[PDB]
Amino acid sequence: KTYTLTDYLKNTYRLKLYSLRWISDHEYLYKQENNILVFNAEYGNSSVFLENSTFDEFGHSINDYSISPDGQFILLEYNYVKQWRHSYTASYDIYDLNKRQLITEERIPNNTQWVTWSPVGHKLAYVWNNDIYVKIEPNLPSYRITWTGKEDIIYNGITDWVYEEEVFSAYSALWWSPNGTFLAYAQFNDTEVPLIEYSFYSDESLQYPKTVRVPYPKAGAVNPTVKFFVVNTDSLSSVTNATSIQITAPASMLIGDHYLCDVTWATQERISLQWLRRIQNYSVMDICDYDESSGRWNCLVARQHIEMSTTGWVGRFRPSEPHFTLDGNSFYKIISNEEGYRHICYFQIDKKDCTFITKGTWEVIGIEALTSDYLYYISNEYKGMPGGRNLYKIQLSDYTKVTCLSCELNPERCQYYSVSFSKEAKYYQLRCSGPGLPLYTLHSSVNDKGLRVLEDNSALDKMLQNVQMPSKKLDFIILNETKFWYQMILPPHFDKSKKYPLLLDVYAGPCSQKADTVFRLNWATYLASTENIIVASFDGRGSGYQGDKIMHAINRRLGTFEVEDQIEAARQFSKMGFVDNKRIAIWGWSYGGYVTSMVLGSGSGVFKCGIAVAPVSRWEYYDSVYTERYMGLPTPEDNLDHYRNSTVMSRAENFKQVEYLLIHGTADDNVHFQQSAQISKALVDVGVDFQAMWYTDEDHGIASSTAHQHIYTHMSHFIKQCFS
Amino acid sequence: KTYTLTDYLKNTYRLKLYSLRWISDHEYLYKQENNILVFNAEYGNSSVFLENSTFDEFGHSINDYSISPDGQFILLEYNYVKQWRHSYTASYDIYDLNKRQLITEERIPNNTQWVTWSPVGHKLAYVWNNDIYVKIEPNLPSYRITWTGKEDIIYNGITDWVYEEEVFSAYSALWWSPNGTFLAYAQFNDTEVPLIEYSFYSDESLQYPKTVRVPYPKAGAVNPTVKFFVVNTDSLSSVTNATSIQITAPASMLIGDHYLCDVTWATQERISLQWLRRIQNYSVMDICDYDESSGRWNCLVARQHIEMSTTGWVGRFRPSEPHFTLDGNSFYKIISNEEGYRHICYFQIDKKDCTFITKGTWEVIGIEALTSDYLYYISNEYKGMPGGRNLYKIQLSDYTKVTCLSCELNPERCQYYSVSFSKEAKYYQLRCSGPGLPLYTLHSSVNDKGLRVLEDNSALDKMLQNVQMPSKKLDFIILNETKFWYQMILPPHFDKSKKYPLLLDVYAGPCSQKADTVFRLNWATYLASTENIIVASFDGRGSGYQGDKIMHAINRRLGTFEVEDQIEAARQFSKMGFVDNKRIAIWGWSYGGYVTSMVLGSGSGVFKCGIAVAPVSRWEYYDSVYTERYMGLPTPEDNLDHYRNSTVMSRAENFKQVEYLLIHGTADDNVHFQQSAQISKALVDVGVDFQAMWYTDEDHGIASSTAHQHIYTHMSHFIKQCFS
Ligand SMILES: Cc1cccc(-c2cn(CC[C@H](N)Cc3cc(F)c(F)cc3F)nn2)c1
Ligand SMILES: Cc1cccc(-c2cn(CC[C@H](N)Cc3cc(F)c(F)cc3F)nn2)c1
């Protein structure tokens, strides 16, 4: 027997996670059956912290919970209702743990946009009708910090669409100070930002389709504007509209259009900000101190740091976040060095220069933890593989004393690690994601002994010995004087002498990685396992984690190299001779659907067919923060030329040579139906036949249970047919 | 060689028309090459009336012309820009024929909604920004009759969406009196009518899709309201806002929601109106006289005639129009008699009863002309075939003296006639549409001698002897004690002993006729001629021209009998044994996409596959005037039950048994994309795979040159594949 489509769609073979949240420097919470336990890492003893039956009469299905850091209250999120990618609304009840009662006085209102405890104690900040509210005690009246909030226009403590998706990667635009004194929050004015309008159809009952209106800046459109504020949460008059002290931006930003692009507190009275120019090659960091006499905030022009690039844009998707030392007089931050590799730079608050505390022909991925002794960072250094991911520690007193904590823990089973440290970094969890089965283990920082194995998925391991799994090959090939990685999913019993049909699975977007050591059970597993199809991927130019020379190659050039390298990557898989070069296909979502579409439109004749799911078809239709970061402005002085030269529509003719399946969700707020509807029109105009499928009311994920099954079923038929 | 798809899509074999407009009782205008001639029917001589080169320096491509009845001016329509089905906007220049100059003073404004001469002389009424304007002389200032016009809200002299499509079948809501004294006009208030909102995507250039908003009453929603007015076009103060004398409705109408449903002038000072209840089983005619002393209008309660039905709705799609005798004291009107057959009733203005001047088991189609001696009517009496159409005359002095003027003119070539009479009915054109090649001939009423053959399409006839045409069989079958007509397009050399694959071509709507004697060169021609496929059609219950017993069968029952009869019709075609009963398909547009969808969802297992093009999926989504005319109100007291029991969505499951192609234009204002999008969602919910195709910016006709070709190409592959 074999890994079938239903196996994938019905999820018959489960991967197991181990999901914990650290509540102290030695205690974390795990959920079990329905009980919330608390595992003491020190001894190993675990205690029922909350019992499955504690909420049987609660009367509502509970979507999420949040426990106040001081263990005194638990937040109960129910009535969840997704909005965009990270945003949603909900209702909230607070339960008193000291007692055993749900607070009925001054409750958090229905339809709340965001909720959060202070990092210490049990204060609540919560946004509602676009306005911030603070609650020092669960049962007491709430101090309404903001008054200006207005639907689709003013955003207080929450991001508008473009800031949510493309900048902060969350819905929440607020930030407590490390002890809970100050509530930093940002403000978004969307007044002159244009609306995207699309239909929502709803239940068959709904007689007129709703029109959905979203402030969405397409490329070169009018952006939102931001203002930043800080509030003292202590001095809160039960009888005066609280004073929000605005920090303004540097004057190098205030000349032109800008985005606030990071908010990191350093100390109890020192906050750092990072600003980005609308042209995203120039960033500025500010450090703002609290002047205890004036109640104001002061950002010294001598404490400013500038980050800029000449070969492309600043950061991977934004500038990295700083990691301040206990005192808050120095920080660590990832930057690309002179050779273009993202490493750790050591900064003194008021010194313009930094010191690199790593270098190499590889990249730091992220700074994970910082003690007085150690900085922990994840990097793809080990075995020189960029698809890999490991935990290291560097000695703060000695920059040449680097230990790899994970490299050797299980060499064969484990090459992709992520880490979760406890408060003050006493203990850490290591998550292994491949190439073997996921493996979750606990560790103490002190001497690095492996206390316990929390999850090894042996349960699944048993189940899979009965199933003909595909194998995964990860390797590289040299194109110029650069090595480019690829990965194949090989059908079980892979006979290198036969000729297999290949499916080129595509993303390709700037700073992507589709070739890694991760263990996945997805659609490709089924395509190899059962249909004996090689599903390949290739991280050519534009892609991440291999230094700026590669990643910035597509600067102001989207839809060129990344596209051509994908074709090349296919030519080469044919030169390996286990590939039926008359049955090569291509497929992709989001950016990858664009690249898929661009490829079929190239008339390279390498490819028989392709599926583009929710593709971008023309950069001008995509949002500004993303598009511009790579292409600049679409005016004839900036880059309007490459904008006009890189559409799927102009390659319409060549589709005559291919079989094409274009699939789009009608209620995609992210890559709007328009992109796909302009392609279809284009093809129809030049008399190209193709295949289409819309998905009513689906968004960019086409992720509803039934549509997920439908789309994948539909694509399989398409692929099968295409390949006989 | 054979009739191929391209032959149909590139229109290589042309049918020729003969398009003339009568300007007198003996002269008509024909266009030739680019010259407008005038053929005198009296002698036969023809003269250049306007020369092809008269407008070479005109500077604009001329979409249409209109010549004033008194030969003095010609109206020049250019910059045409389609709106809905009949509606559009344009610009207009007026050219003086007496002289040779384009009037430059007081020109008709850009973006005019409607324009028309008075029936006599050369006055102009023209609607613009929703308001009426009169012009007694081309060069003189225009008297603005209305002031209340407002976009999407107030319609003066033009119909709103639902009145255009479903009532008057034109854009123009105005009516001159027979000599040009009075301008009758209607007014539409759409204030509380709900909007349909859909996207338009436009040229690739357009960066945000436009949202299109249209006042559109779905079933049971708030209807537009109407008021009627008459103006004296002579007494027009170059210094006073002209007085519009409102006629109001009967009081039997004013109790509830109503529509104005006909406007026929009787004499120079007597206008007739017809009113319809929102429940469309009750009509009332009014006759309104001009009181020369009061300047008012008076509709005598004794001159009212009531039209109503108990077994269904009044009229075929509306009540028929009256035909008033010279004096205006009697009129002729078509009504169904006691046995349910539409015949001519003779009415005296103030007498409640009428006299039937025809009876039979067949129907009058329309009253074409009326003299002091004769009434001319078209009917399907000849050979007892309802798919036929003939010209007859009845003697006004003797109701038993009926002559058929066409029946015998060419029995084999000619069984479908239409007629165009000259002023006072001195001469007429006969248009033969099948079953042979279209034949256009001229005739004098006086003794009925056939002056000349104007067009015989012998040019095409030559061309087609070289091509393997399909033959067409029209016949009937008995189901209960009723005979139901069907037609087959049979592949050339049709061997009755073989087993052919059949495609059931569906419309099926209330009062439809898909089985007739007409000669067509369409898609079916290609399917039979080249793919040797039988393309059948069948007019079962609900269908027109065979009396109320059949047509009213579906009253309050849409999506039942008409649907079941179509399945039946296919069972029976299998019993004829030349049909491969494992390769039967079904297809349909508009209503027929609905019926096609209902059938596949019936699980009758007769049908392998089907194509539904722009179907209705649920009656509550279609406009009110149509839907209600057949189903009543969708409230639980009226008919909400049949409404909820007749959706395509509830048959979702059964689609498992079929192969389905659903095709819809995104910018369909008539059957909104919602209808299709609710189907696709329904199918995806029960995990049925199917095939889809949207058409960017196309409407209900998918009729742009490139989309037309694309859709039909696409459906062919589908059909071919479905049939191997
Ligand atoms: C692994 C990792 C870590 C942190 C940030 C990110 C990340 C990923 N992204 C992508 C955001 C962007 N909206 C993706 C996107 C690209 C398209 F081209 C498109 F059409 C739609 C998209 F959502 N931004 N930041 C990824
Ligand atoms: C031959 C002839 C003479 C006069 C009027 C008409 C006539 C034809 N029609 C059809 C109009 C109707 N809206 C068609 C239609 C039906 C549907 F069910 C639908 F979903 C969409 C449509 F356009 N109404 N009146 C036909």
Image (cartoon, coloured by chain):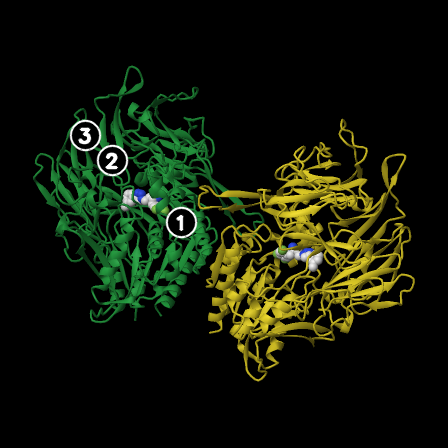
Chain colours: A green, B yellow
Determine the secondary structure under disc 3.
loop
Q: Name the residue type under label 1.
A: His
Q: Which chain carries label 2?
A: A
- Tell me which corner region of the image, top left, top right, bottom left or bottom right, holds residue A633: top left
| Residue at mark 2 shares a chain with residue at mark 3 | yes
Name which residue lies at 64% across and 51% down: B623
Which residue is tagged 3?
A: A326
Tell me which amino acid carries mark 3.
Answer: Leu
Seen in the picture, residue A557 relative to A323 is either above or below; the reply is below
- Which residue is tagged 2? A321
- Residue at mark 3: chain: A
Q: Name the residue under label 1.
A: A700
Residue A526 at x, y percent in the picture: 32, 64
Q: Is mark 1 within 8 Å of ligand 1?
A: yes
Earlier sequence position, callout 2 versus callout 1: 2
Residue B569 coordinates in the image, percent (x, y): 63, 73
Quadrant housing residue B493: bottom right
**Among all residues in the image, which is located at the extreme top?**
A293
